[PDB]
Structure formats: structure tokens, C-alpha cells
Amino acid sequence: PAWLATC
Amino acid sequence: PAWLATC
Amino acid sequence: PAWLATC
Amino acid sequence: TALVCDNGSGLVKAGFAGDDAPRAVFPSIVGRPRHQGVMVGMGQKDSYVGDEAQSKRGILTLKYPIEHGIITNWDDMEKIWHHTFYNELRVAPEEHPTLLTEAPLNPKANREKMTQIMFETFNVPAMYVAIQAVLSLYASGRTTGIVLDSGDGVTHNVPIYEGYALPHAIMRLDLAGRDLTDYLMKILTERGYSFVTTAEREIVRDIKEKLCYVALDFENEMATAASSSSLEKSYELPDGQVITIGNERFRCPETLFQPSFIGMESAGIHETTYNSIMKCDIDIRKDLYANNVMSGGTTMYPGIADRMQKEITALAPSTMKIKIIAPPERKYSVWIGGSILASLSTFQQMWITKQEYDEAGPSIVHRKC
Amino acid sequence: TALVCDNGSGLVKAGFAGDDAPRAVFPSIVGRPRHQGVMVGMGQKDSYVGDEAQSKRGILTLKYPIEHGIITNWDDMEKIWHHTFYNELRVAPEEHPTLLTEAPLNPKANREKMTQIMFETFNVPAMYVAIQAVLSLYASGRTTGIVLDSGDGVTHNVPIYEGYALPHAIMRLDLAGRDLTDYLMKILTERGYSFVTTAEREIVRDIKEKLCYVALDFENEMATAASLEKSYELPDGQVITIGNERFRCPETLFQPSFIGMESAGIHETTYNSIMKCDIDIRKDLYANNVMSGGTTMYPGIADRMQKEITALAPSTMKIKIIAPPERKYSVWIGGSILASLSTFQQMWITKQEYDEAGPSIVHRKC
Amino acid sequence: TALVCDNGSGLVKAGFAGDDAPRAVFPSIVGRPRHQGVMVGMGQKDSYVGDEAQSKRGILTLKYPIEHGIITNWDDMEKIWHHTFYNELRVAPEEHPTLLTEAPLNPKANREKMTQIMFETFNVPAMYVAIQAVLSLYASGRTTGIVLDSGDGVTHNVPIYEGYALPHAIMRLDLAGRDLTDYLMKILTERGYSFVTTAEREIVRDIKEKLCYVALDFENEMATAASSSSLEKSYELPDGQVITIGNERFRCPETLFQPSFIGMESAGIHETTYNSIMKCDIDIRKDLYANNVMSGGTTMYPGIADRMQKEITALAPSTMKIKIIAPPERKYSVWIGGSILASLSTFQQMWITKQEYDEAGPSIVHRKC
Amino acid sequence: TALVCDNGSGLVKAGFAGDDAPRAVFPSIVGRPRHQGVMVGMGQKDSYVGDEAQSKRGILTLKYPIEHGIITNWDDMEKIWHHTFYNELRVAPEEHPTLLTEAPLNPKANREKMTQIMFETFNVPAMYVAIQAVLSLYASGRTTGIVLDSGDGVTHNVPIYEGYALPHAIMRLDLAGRDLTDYLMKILTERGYSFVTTAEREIVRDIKEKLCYVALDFENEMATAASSSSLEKSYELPDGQVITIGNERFRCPETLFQPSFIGMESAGIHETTYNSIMKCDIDIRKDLYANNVMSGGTTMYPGIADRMQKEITALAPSTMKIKIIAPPERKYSVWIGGSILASLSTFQQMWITKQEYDEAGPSIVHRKC
Amino acid sequence: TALVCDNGSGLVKAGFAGDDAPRAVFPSIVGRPRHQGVMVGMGQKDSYVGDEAQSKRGILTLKYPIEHGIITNWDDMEKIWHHTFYNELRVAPEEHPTLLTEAPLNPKANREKMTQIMFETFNVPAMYVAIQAVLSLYASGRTTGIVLDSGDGVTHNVPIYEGYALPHAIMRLDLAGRDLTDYLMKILTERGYSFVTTAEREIVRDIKEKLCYVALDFENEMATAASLEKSYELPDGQVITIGNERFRCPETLFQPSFIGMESAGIHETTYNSIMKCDIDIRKDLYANNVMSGGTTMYPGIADRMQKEITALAPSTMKIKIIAPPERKYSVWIGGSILASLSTFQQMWITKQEYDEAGPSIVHRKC
Ligand SMILES: Nc1ncnc2c1ncn2[C@@H]1O[C@H](COP(=O)(O)OP(=O)(O)O)[C@@H](O)[C@H]1O
Ligand SMILES: Nc1ncnc2c1ncn2[C@@H]1O[C@H](COP(=O)(O)OP(=O)(O)O)[C@@H](O)[C@H]1O
Ligand SMILES: Nc1ncnc2c1ncn2[C@@H]1O[C@H](COP(=O)(O)OP(=O)(O)O)[C@@H](O)[C@H]1O
Ligand SMILES: Nc1ncnc2c1ncn2[C@@H]1O[C@H](COP(=O)(O)OP(=O)(O)O)[C@@H](O)[C@H]1O
Ligand SMILES: Nc1ncnc2c1ncn2[C@@H]1O[C@H](COP(=O)(O)OP(=O)(O)O)[C@@H](O)[C@H]1O
Ligand SMILES: [Mg+2]
Ligand SMILES: [Mg+2]
Ligand SMILES: [Mg+2]
Ligand SMILES: [Mg+2]
Ligand SMILES: [Mg+2]
């Protein structure tokens, strides 16, 4: 979620 | 009573 | 409401 | 032959395993009389239950035993199961397995007490309690999709990829078709119509499920209907009066996509599906975006099935197509899935038996199902 | 065998249970002599109760013991009950259960004193007191409808849906036949005839009972009447002619403002009685309007009430004014029904309960 | 200088913004003479309004324009506003603002037509319609509390935590002193006294206002009064006859805590305050339990605050303290709060001016109030 | 005098260098009001930030600007930095140098935008951003150990032999106390207690902080609690209710040692520490096994400090000595190490000054740290 | 007809001898389901091997059975061999002779257990385990060269003059594409992309295969990039942009200090393996530099070696880096060449030889 790509 | 419909 | 605790 | 009961919080849908339509459809209410009965030799027994307690609506106190999926009053839910097995189906439950149902993320006392009542007060030979949103995939036949169930108390997404469900990504929202009725009966007041009691909740629900539709652009529709346009709908009350609800016809199910109307902090059903997809893995997401299965009675509006496809595409990636599967016999889909699942030769070893029950107690549904 | 005594306020309609017409029908007046007798070797006892007072009417003063449903004089209501038991039905009441009656929304001293008299004076084994409109719905066989009772003191609506009465919506109005008799003998004075005393009231009542009729369109009849006359023969060879005052006398039922009553007519204490019921109940309470009592026997009302409730009820709802032709004794027919059911034998007020709790058990039961 | 007219449904309490007590306290009744006057001098008039209709009570037909908070008759409510502005306050409304009032959950036609009459007939410079249970909190000076208001019609319940009112938990009931008078004059007939007319409602109301009291334990008081005790109170009529009601003085206000006497399906005013608290958040409940403001006329019974505390302590958790506040000047509390709220320098930008009304008509009140 | 702040995703710990305890401990939440405020004449600012937003949390919509160590929103993070400098510390930032922190393996945009906001908005003379796991070794005083820092979003394993970090052997895991609070409020629903909103997430965190312990033998504890035993613990909600949780006391911090409960594929903290040790050299391992430092808030359970020593000795060589260095003041250990490192004469030339910043822009943070 | 399989640490390449390209390649992956299967029709097979495990990445926990050439888990390797025979070629192993392979300087337990499994489970009539780097020279046709094999686990140089492989001048370096992918998914963390799981390592490998290229002048490229940007689309619809981190990933092959290795690059271990030979051999070993494997398929790997070995070579020496375009399956091509020889026909290991002295016959016959 918080990143950019994954999670 | 005295509403527009019910009561 | 209708649970056990909250709601 | 097995029995497929679907205990909803507002509609009991029962029948036999192997059919294609539920044989017993009647609401889940138990009516108590609240008035002085002065006759004699009269058939006013004690308490009416089901569709019998909708004819004598003006005298009765209509109580729903199930609320938000969980069961609150266990004495009259026993009455509803007794009425369903005898007066509406006419079958002895000592000769039939029974396939029950439950919303996910429920309290664990419901499974145990439902098993204890079905095994000790009804003496079924076998029983099994499933999860609602799994069965809507059995009904569609596919085994890949994210099932959006709704209808009278519970609204929950369960993603399933290839027969493997992801329980770390299931969501559950308590915003289904009871809060829409209680919001419609409160937004009706500002026009002039004051429906208050439990007998008038049925009239508000009968308004809701045949006039209310879901808008596409809510801010465009609230400016269109603000002009004197062709949106009003006269509805004939059971005493004779007509009521013209023009503007509060799409404001009732726009609560489903903006839950701040009742003061809930949550996001709408278009965003507990996107988050429930984004909690799944990257290989799973591509053909979870393309299989959105709707279910339940609340998803039977003239709108939503092409409004979810507009709201999810606003926050999905651009090169990922969406297909909201609306199989328009979807109101009984959680029963069609139970009729399919109970009629399989692969399934018959999954039944909780009586000999398992007397050696494990009602704590065996936590390790089964 | 039980006793069904519809102890009304204009006449006493008593009889035996299980039948379909009362044995005793006679007015409830206790006439007393007012002049001085001179013939020594005669009768002339002390007082004449019933139709004997109508026979010796000119020498008498006729007192009504019941006024607007409540019993005002207990010393001769005991006389009327004694007369109806012995001299008219000829039964010792120590071997018979009795079924009394009462208008709704009454003072609760009546329910106590009637029970106290029926147990401590006549020694009834077991009694019960009903309501005049539940029995009127028992008579028609239904269990669904709204009743409208009338006759010398009370006019009340008791709506029942399925045996479940709605006791927060029982309108009571005191505008029955005695207040029409007293308006007829007041509106006849403009023509010239002056009826004053109690015998003249008993003549004006007989004028009302056969020459008066309810109009349909009141202003149309008041315009037609200025162009319809009748002729009643007084009991000494004399004729009067009432032309206009035969629909103005029962028009007070639909317009109570003629005697200064603030309340609305009987077409608006039925609509307002339905409009306090619930929206499921109104759909058939519109379509089941039972009628009972004496003052609904005009050649009018049963077509005028439909005409003036159809202008108040919503236009998509049909209205059936159920007017049985044998409706004058409908409360008694319902009482003979209600005392002939095997479900009812555990509903009486036995002598043991009266010895245990006293006459305060009548509000507890019934 | 602004004007504060708490236009109630049973009493019109108007005055000047800045004081602490209303100048004009008089009921809202318009009397039409039902009799025939024969005196060729002056002798009579056409329609008396206010306390003239209570002075000439015998020959008149007393008619309340407002029923249950909603205005039903706009012709004589204009007469009552005209009477209050001229004959009782002696001002010109073209040089004064006006702070009106309204119960929560009303039809929008009240808010529209009240603005239209105040601007197009009396020609006020500015106006603003408040809501009653906010102004009781303004009068008490708090910002945290759940306000119970009553008096001749509506009985509503508005919870406010820090100024942020929670409008999804505002219960509204119609069980106030009008419906208590119509039950007292129906339970008096059991004793023998038959009060019928509209002039004789103003005597049963005067019986209620000084003999009726709220019990503590209702089933204990109904067993105490079964013996002849000190509950009897002799009240005399306008003519010299006396009546003695012993038992029916804690059964008229018992309809508040038990609405099943009048056939209402609702629960009592303690339960629609416990439910109004339980629809709030867990942080808010702790200091809404300890701040219970009572307002309105029908809360001036003797034992009402102790009965409310006893019947909320059985519903709240035992480790949470309750404090039913009740000032002695709670009858005019809405007017005191109106005089406070109109006398703020913060508020002078919150008026609906004439210039806003000229450009969008009487529809700015929904977006401005 | 220099400033040492510890920007975590949970609490913000700040103060002056040279001390031994932070002056300012308050959570990193910014709350927005979601209800309509009608108490005109009050103080109702549009954004509450800090422990005051935890005080008035029943109205607010609480939101953490940091998720999993990285900053999602810079608008209400500048609010928290402004509140920390001004309201809670009462110092202008134009005089003092600042010392921030960062989790390892974070994106470069965090360092760049943090430098840009600290220099071009608060105008500090000098700044420096360290790594959150070196400072625990600095506070412990050792130059040898493998630091396990874990609180609210991240979990590191940074080995340092003698002042030489091994960047090919650091392990980052996103499994700290935020996911434990979410799993606790998802597993409480099985018993009956249903916590949904952010205002109830803040209650479930307070349940977790004072009732959850880490088990030693998980199967034996799950077999013990299956019998009716003394593992139950009652907790009182802020409105008055009591909740009893018997089994989910160790099931909430068992996700740290079995991350397959929340659906994570990774290995537990006992195995990532072992893999971080085995990624080092053989001469380094002999005294990396002996010095196992812990830090952060999630290492403050009554369990883990003697379950880690069991689970690493289960898979270490038998002749190797393991000693988990768990000081009791380890919650503020990162700030203690920051206050030590900022009060050094050797560190005084390691600052990123204002002159060298604008000569190279905000990209100097990648080479100077 | 003989069988030639190339059990690499990456993808298993198998097929029939005497052919030119392998029959079917697929990755050496055995995945297990890690979620709860709630269905009854399907959700089966309990473990997926090879290509279906790469198809269902989301459910499965993929796990390679070979790490740096050695075989850690023997159970799933039996699954992979059984799949590669049966489901991929549909041949009984009892009929055909099988040609295996092995990286040099492996533990001898690999050869022993490989022989034991290939005889006592598949009943192969004749096996032979070869060495990977000689098969590249057999595919190239020469007998002169130094083979820079580089697959997924291992990377090793074997110099061969004309036959007579020098076993003292052979290096081995564990720095291959798996260690490049584990560094790429750690260098992608700077831009903001976090790949954690095995199913995301299977995406980072796909990013490395088609966007990473070997730079020529590393400092000049690092100064230039501060437009080298490319865009890859993740399989859920999301795009990523990696400009700088596509020549830094294969730069670890020439600077092993990035991932913390003491060793030297492939341009330097090749030079040390050349200089460990005699003096006369270098004049042709410099001129013949064979490369193989999949990790030598970057855009510019051959040019970088040709540039950087000449920086540390004598100036009068010429270097030709033999980079065939079909070098990804060159070890299998050499196996298919070498298995179709009448000279090699006598070089097998029969079942009768294995029945004597157990599985240690490959320690003398290989
Ligand atoms: N045609 C309809 N249109 C919109 N809503 C409907 C319609 N029919 C039923 N509903 C709503 O769905 C609810 C019942 O549907 P259902 O999904 O079967 O509930 P449950 O799962 O509890 O059995 C009703 O309460 C009603 O609010
Ligand atoms: N055919 C009639 N037409 C008009 N009025 C009648 C008629 N018959 C009876 N009445 C009136 O009704 C009164 C008696 O009716 P009844 O219902 O028996 O009164 P109660 O029930 O109190 O005994 C009479 O006094 C008379 O005024
Ligand atoms: N001292 C009192 N005791 C009991 N009831 C009262 C008392 N005073 C007024 N009431 C009742 O309250 C009603 C008026 O109260 P009020 O609050 O002024 O109504 P509103 O809010 O509409 O103006 C009256 O009709 C009466 O029934
Ligand atoms: N007494 C406690 N026991 C266990 N966990 C705690 C305790 N106190 C706080 N925590 C957890 O640690 C987190 C905050 O601790 P902290 O190390 O300061 O995080 P950060 O470094 O990001 O600021 C909280 O979210 C909480 O889940
Ligand atoms: N076209 C390519 N470009 C760059 N690297 C590749 C390419 N193809 C494969 N690789 C890398 O080499 C490995 C597989 O190649 P291969 O030599 O066949 O392995 P093995 O020798 O174990 O069979 C993969 O892990 C991948 O990282
Ligand atoms: Mg359902
Ligand atoms: Mg009668
Ligand atoms: Mg008021
Ligand atoms: Mg920290
Ligand atoms: Mg290879």
C-alpha cells in the first residue's frame, strides 16, 4: 500500500 | 395526524 | 448494536 | 435428500437440495400482539411468524431475530426454524441433512448454538454450515472472483482465486438493506410523510424495493431532480393516499457508496472491493479485477451494476479491464450454490455427523467448515 | 340457561339466551301518580313500571332512571330489574346466570353497583357485563369492522380488527334519540304546537319514530320544502302537519351545532375513529361499517353516511355501510350468541369470586 | 436589536434579544365565536387570539394552529405572529431581526413558508431559524450534553459533544402535554367527570399543571393508592363544584415512560435517550451519560428527574455515573438560549439577510440553517 | 544545543541533545472533524494534531501520515513537525540543528523531501538523518551486536561488528505493531467484540499494550487455555462495558514469530535474525550471537525476550552462546542514542550545514549519510 | 536413442540426443499451496512442479531445489525429474540412456545420490554425468578455449588446450543470476518499489531478463544518467520506471563488492585462470574465449570482457570473445553432440557396473 508498487 | 400522510 | 460489545 | 436453508436476517429462503429455486420464501419476523383481544372462540393463538405475520401487520409487534448477521433472540429463531421445517416445507428433520449458512467474521457462538439447536432440538442426522460468499461462486460455476454479497444487515467481500480463499483479505461492512430502509424512513420525513413503527417499516421497505434506483452521477442527478423534472413517482399507500418521492429516490442507495450519510466512518462498497483486491497478490489481482460477482437482494437496483464499473475504474490501473458479473437471478444465488454444493458426491464426507457431535460437542464446527 | 338483559336507556330488551328475539321489550320508565285519588275501593299501588305507565300515562309523572348511559336513580332501577325478572320473564334469578351491558367510557361506579345489586339483592349465581358494540359485531358473525351504536343517551364507535379492539380510538358521543326528541318538541313550537310535559314527550317520540327521516342533500331538501307534508293524529281526535321538521330533527346527528354541541357529527366521529387506527387496519375498517341501535332506523342515514364518508375517505377505497334490517335488537342477538358458546362458561363472574374480592372484581375481569 | 420569538406549539414566548425572560408569554389559540350574538352596540368581534380567547373561553372555539410542531393553519398563525409583534411587544418588525425556532426532523415546508411569511408580509431585515435543543445547551452554557426537550407536541432528543452535533442520532417523539391532556381527560371519565369541549380542554390542562406528578415506582404507587391515602387532591372548577382525583395523577405523566397506554409502539423517554446515547461513539458516551439537560414544559413535573435517573441507571453500565441536570428555569430555556445566541458578535454574520432572499427565494434556509 | 527527534510511525519522541529522556512523547496522528459543528461562539479549529486529537477522538477521523516507515502525506506531517517544534517544545528551529531518523531500505524521496522541508521551511542551520538501528547500539554503548528494532511499521536486523555495518546482511520486515493491532481487532470479532473505526483502533491498541504477552510454548498455551483456566483478563471500555479475552492474549503477538497469520509469506523475527547472522562472516558470528540487542516498542511484551533465546538456540550451533540484550529502557533507546551521538565532539563536523545544502540541492543527503 | 537433460539451477532443459534444440524447457520450481482451499471440485494436486507453478504464482510458495549447483532437497528434485520424463517427454526411462550434467568442484554426494536415484528409481540402462563447461567446447566444435559458463547458480572457467583439461587452473565463483536478481530486488527499493515474496522474485527476474544491460564505461554511464529510462508493466496493470538500476545490476559481475564478496570479477578470474596455465598455452587461450549460459546474454557482456581483459593483457596479444547467439542452450547442444558418438558409446555406465561397488563408480568413470 504505502510504497509505490507493491504493498 | 396533521403531517402530510401518516400521523 | 446487536453484538456483544460495540455496535 | 438434503435440506438447504438460507437463514437471512430479513428473508428465510429454504428448499430441497437439487432443485433450482427455493421452495419456501417468507420474511424472518415473529409478531406479538399488542392489543386487548375481546372475542371468544377466536383463532388468535399466541404469536404469528413469517408471511402469516405480514397479513396481521396492524396489530403485531414485528421483531427480527437476526440483526447484522448475528442472532440476538434464540427463542423465536427456534420458532422460525420450526415454522420453516413444518408449516412451510412439511418434512420431518430426523430424516434429512441440513445445509445452513453464515456470514464471515461472525461471533463464534452462532456456529455452536446453531449446531446445538439443529442437533439436539431438531435431531438432524447430519448438518453443515458454510460461508455465504463462497456459495455465490458455486452458483455462477466459476471458481475465480471476488464475491460482493449484500442484503439486510451484512455486506462482505470474499476473494477466491483458484478454489483457495484469502482470509487475510476478506472485508465485512454492516450497511446492507436495513440501514437503507431506516435512512429512507428518516429522509421521507422532510417531505411530509412520517413513518414510525415496525408496521410502517414494511411500507417503507415496499417503497424502497420498487421505486429506488442508483444514480450514475450523483451531483448531476441532484441538480437534475432539483428542477421540476420527470423523476417523481406516486406510490399508493395501503389506506389510499399517494406519496410523491422525487428527490429521495436515489439518495436512499447512495448511502451504499457514501456511508457518511449515517455517520459511518467506512468507505463505500466500491472501495471495500478495491481494497479487498489490493490486499491480494499481484498474479491474483488481474483476474480478480475481471470477475466481480454480485449477490444478495440489496444488489438488485436499476443502477449499481454499471456504477461499480464506473467507480472501480477510477481507481484501478488503466490497462486492467473490469467485468461486474450481474447474473440477474442473483437474489437466490446463495441458495442455488447450496443446492449445487449439497448435491455433489465429492461433498458427502464433509457432513458433521451425529456420532461426531456426541463425542466433540458443539465445538466441532470451529474445526470443520 | 343464561339471561341476556340488554338494559338499555330507552327501553329494556331482555330475554333468554340461545333465542333470536327478546321476550321482553318495554320502555324503562317508573311512573308515579301526581294527582289525588278519590275512588277508595281500587288499586293504584304506588308506582307503575314499564308499559303499565304508558297505559296510565295521563295521570303520571314519567321518570327515566338512565341518563346518557349512566344510572342516575338506583332505587327504581332495582324496580325495573325486579319487574323484568318476575312480572315479565317469570323466573327466579337464583337459578340463572345474567349478562348485563354497558356503554364504553362510563364511570366505573356502574360496574360495581350493578354487580353489587345483582349479587346482594337478586342472588344471581354468576354474572357478566359486556360492551354494547362488541356484541353488535358478534351479531353479524364478523370479527372485523367498526360499529356505531345509538339510542337514547349514547352514540359510540368501537373499532375491532380481528378480535383485537383498539381501545385508544373509541369515540363516545352523547347525542342519541332523547336529544332528538327534545329538539323535535322544541322545533315544533314554531309551527304552533306546544308539547311540554312527560306525556307530551312520549307523544313527540312517537311522532319522531314514524314521520322523521334523514335527508340526503340537506340544502336541497330545505329548498324543496319551500314549495312533503305529513299528518299525525294526536290521541284526542286532533291532527298536526309537520312539513319541514322531519329531516331537521335527525339532521342534528350530522350537525350537532343545532343544540350548541361543539363536537362533530356521526360522520366525523367515525372517520376520526378510523384515522386513529393503523394503515393496515383502515383498509377494511373503511369497508366494514356495522350499524346498530334504535336511532339508525331512519329511511335516510345508511345512504347518507356512505355519501358523507366517501367525501372524507380517500377516493381509491370502497366503503360498505353494513346496515342489517334486524339491527334494533342486534346487541341482544349478540348477547344470546355470546352466552351460548362453550368457550364462554369459564368467563363468568362467579359468586365465590365476589365473596373473595367484592364488587371491585368487575374492572379486573370483563 | 434582534427579536427572539420561541414560537411554540402550545405557548408563544417572545421578547427582546439580550434579556433573561420573555416579555410576552401567552398561548397560541385563535377563538372563533360559535354562538349567535344579539347586541347592537359593539358587543362582540370577529376572532380573538391569545389570552383574549382564554378570557372569552365559554362562547368561543379554541383552535391550535400548530399540531406536533408542524404548522397546520397558516392563516391564523399569521394572526398570532401579528398579535405578538404589535399588540404584545409593540414594535415594528421592519427594523428588527428575528430568531425563530423549529423542532428537528420537520417537513421543509415549515422552513420555507416561515421565511416567506417573515420576509414578504412583515418585511423583516434579517431572520434565522434555530433548532430548539441546541438553544437549551446555549442557555445552560455547556457544549457537551444530550438535550431532552418537551412541551405540547414534540419530544425530541439531540446529542452534542463539542459543538459537533451528531445528526444521525436525533430521536424525535410526539408524546408531550397535549397528548397527556387528551389522556387525562379520558381517564377522568372513569371517575365520572366528563370533559369534552375545546373550552374544557383548558380545564383538564389546569388540572394537569398543578395536581399531576411523576411517581417513583409505578406499581408501588398503584398499590399505595389502592388504600385511601393522601394522594387525593380536591380541585374546583370555574364554577364552585369540586372534583377529587386520587389515582389518576401519576397515570397522566406515566404515559411518558410507558407509551403503550395510548397505543403507541414507541418506548419511553428514558429508552429513547439510552438509544440516542448508544448510537454515539465510545468516547462520546462517557460524558454524554454525565450531562443530561432537560428542557420544555412537560419536564416540570415533580418526580421526573429522579425517575429518569432511576430508569437510565438500570440501562447504563454500573461503573458509569449519570447526572440528570435540571435547572429551575428550564421552561423558558429555549428563549434564554435564543437571547444568548442572538447577542453574540460571532453570530451577526450568520443572519439570512434580505439580499440573499431576493436572489434565490425561500430556499436558502435549507443551505443556511 | 542540537535537537533530536525520532519520527516514528507511532509516537513522536523529541527533545534536546544531552538529556536522557525525550521531552515530547505524543502520537503522530492528525484528526479532522467529520461532523457538523453548531455551537457558534466556540473554538473549533479544522485540524487537531497530537495527543489533543487523541483526547477529542470521538468526533475526529484519526490518520497517521507515516505507513510502514515511509511518509505517505507531507501536508499533515509538516503539521506534526510544526507542532513538535512550537507547541510541545517552545523553541524556534532557526537556531538549533536537528537530528532525524529513518528506517533502512527506504526510498530516497523520504531523505530528499525531509531535507527540503527541514531546510527550506523551518530554516535550521544544520541537519543530519541517521539510521534507526545504529542508534540503539550507540545507546547500549557497544560497538558489536545485531540490532532488532521494531515498532509500528518496520522491523530491522542490522549487524555491526566493530563500527563497520554490513549492508549486504540487513533484513527489513514490515510486520510491527500496526499489523498486530489490526489482527487483534480482527480476531476479537470471533468472541463478539466488534471494533471498526479508527477511534476503536486506538482502543484495541490500548488493549494490546497492557494485556498481551508472548507465549513460550504456543501449542501448550493453546492447550492450556482450552480448559477453563486463569488466562482470562477483563478490560473496561471507556464507556463502561467490560470485555474478557482469554485466548487472544498470545495469539496477537504470535504473528511476530509466525507471519502466516496475517497472510505474509515471510519468516518470523527469530529466523530473519538468524539469516542476518548467517549472512555475516564466520569470525563475526561468534560474537554476533552473543550480543543480540532489542529496541522499539513491539519488543516490550512480557514474553519475547526469553522466547527469542529459545527459538534462536533451537537453530544455532550447540556450542555457541546467545544472550538477548533486552534493557528495560529500550522503548526510547533510539532517542537516547541520538542524544548521545549529537553530544559528541567527533560528530560536530558530520552535519549537513546550510551553506553546503544550496550548493548541491537536496541530493547531498545521499552522499553525506 | 539417448536422453540429454541439463539440470541447471535455473530452468531444466531436456530432450533427445542427436537433435539441435531441447524438446521443452521449464523452470526448476516446485511450489506448494499456502492458503486454505474451500471447494470440492478442484483445488487439487497438492504440489505443482515446473510450469504450472509459474502459472499460479499467487497461491504458491515457490522453492528452488538447487542452490549454487548443489541439490539441497532431494524429494522435489525427484518430482522434477519424474515430471521432466513423464509429463514432458512421455518416455519410459527404462528404455533410453540418460546424460546428466554437473557443475565442477561440487561435492561428490551429488554424483553419488544422482547415480543412486537414476538407477534405483528410474531403472535407466546407462547414465553418464558430464561437466558443464566441456559441453560448451563440444558445442563450439573446438578443442581450444576457456569456457566462461554462467548460469543461475554457478560461474566457472575451465581451460582446455586440445583436450587435456587442466584441473589446477579452474576457478568457480557463485555470483550468478540468482545473486543478481536478489540484488536487483534490493536496488529497486530506492525508487519506491518493494518486491518481497517468491512470486515477486519471479517478476524481478523477468525485469532483469529484458531491461538490464551491461554498461561499457560505468562511471561515464553513472554521470550520463544524472535519458536511460525504460518502463516495465507489472502484471496487475501498474507500470514502473527504472533508469539507473539496469546497468548497476549486471555490474556486480565485474565488481562483486556490491553484494559483499571478497572475490574478483569475471574479467579477472578469467585472467587468473589463464595465468595459472603454462606459457605456450596462453597464446591461443587468449584468442579463444567461449561463453555460455543465460547470464552471458546481456546486451554488452562480450564487449565489456573484450575491453577489460586487454587492460591487463600484454599489448602484443589478441583476444577474441566467442559469443554465439545460440549460447543459452549451448551446454545441451554439446550434450546432444557428445551423446551421438560411437567413441562415447563405449563410455557409458551400465547397470551391471553400478551393481558392483555401489554408486561410487562415478568417482573413477567420470
Ligand atoms: N427488488 C429489490 N430491490 C432492492 N432491494 C431489495 C429488493 N428485494 C429485496 N431487497 C432488499 O434485500 C433484502 C433481502 O434480500 P436478501 O439478499 O435475500 O437478504 P438476506 O441475505 O438476509 O437473506 C431486503 O431486506 C431488501 O432491503
Ligand atoms: N324507527 C325509529 N326511527 C327513529 N327513531 C327510533 C326508531 N326506533 C327507535 N327509535 C329511537 O331509539 C330509541 C330506542 O332505541 P334503543 O336502541 O333500543 O335504545 P337503548 O338501547 O338505550 O334501549 C327510542 O327512544 C327512539 O328515540
Ligand atoms: N408547571 C407545568 N407542569 C406540568 N406541565 C406543564 C407545566 N407547564 C406547562 N406544562 C405543559 O407544557 C405545555 C407547554 O409547555 P412549553 O414548553 O411552553 O411548549 P412549547 O415548547 O411548544 O412552547 C403545556 O401545554 C402543558 O401541557
Ligand atoms: N507496553 C507495550 N507493549 C507492547 N507494545 C507496545 C507497548 N507500547 C507501545 N507498543 C507498540 O509500539 C508501538 C510504538 O512504539 P515505538 O517503538 O515508539 O514506534 P516508533 O519507533 O515507530 O515510534 C505502538 O504502536 C504499540 O503497538
Ligand atoms: N536473456 C537473458 N538475459 C539476461 N539474463 C538471463 C537471460 N535469460 C536467463 N537469464 C538469467 O540466467 C538464468 C537462467 O539461465 P541458464 O544459463 O539457462 O541457467 P542454468 O545454467 O541453471 O540452466 C536466469 O536466472 C536469469 O537470471
Ligand atoms: Mg443472504
Ligand atoms: Mg342500545
Ligand atoms: Mg419548545
Ligand atoms: Mg523506532
Ligand atoms: Mg548452465
Image (cartoon, coloured by chain):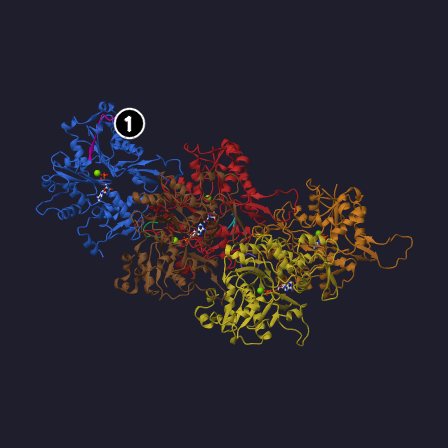
Chain colours: A green, B purple, C cyan, D red, E orange, F yellow, G brown, H blue
Q: Name the quadrant containing residue F215.
A: bottom right
Rendered location of residue F367, percent (x, y): 46, 64
Of the pair G4 and F285, the residue shown nearer to us = G4
Q: Is residue D229 magenta-colored?
A: no
Badge 1: how crowded within 10 Å, few (<14), some, or many (20+)?
A: few
* Left or right of residue G240: residue H290: left
Chain of the residue on which disc 1 is drawn: H
Please say if D9 is above or below E211. Answer: above
- Residue extent of the magenta highlight: H120-131
Q: Would residue E137 appear left or right of H101 to someone viewing this image?
A: right
Exactly how many numbered labels are in the figure? 1
On the image, the x and y values in percent for residue G250 come to 46, 44
Q: Amino acid at mark 1?
A: Thr
Q: For disc 1, does the CB lie below 8 Å from ligand 5? A: no
Residue D195 visible in rendering: no
Q: Is D171 or E120 nearer to us in this picture?
A: D171
Please give left or right for residue F330 compared with residue D256 in the image: right
The outermost residue toward the right is E40
Residue situated in front as seen by the camera: H94 or H180: H180
Q: In the rendered view, would you say D91 is above or below G147? A: above
Q: Secondary structure at mark 1?
A: loop
Q: Position of residue H243 (x, y in %)?
A: 24, 53
Residue F269 visible in the shown view: yes
Residue positioned most to the left:
H316
Is residue H129 on the magenta stretch?
yes
Ligand 8 placement by image quarter = bottom right
* Residue G260 % position (x, y): 39, 42
Residue linked to disc 1: H121
Quarter of the view holding residue E31? bottom right
Q: Is F72 or G176 nearer to us in this picture?
A: G176
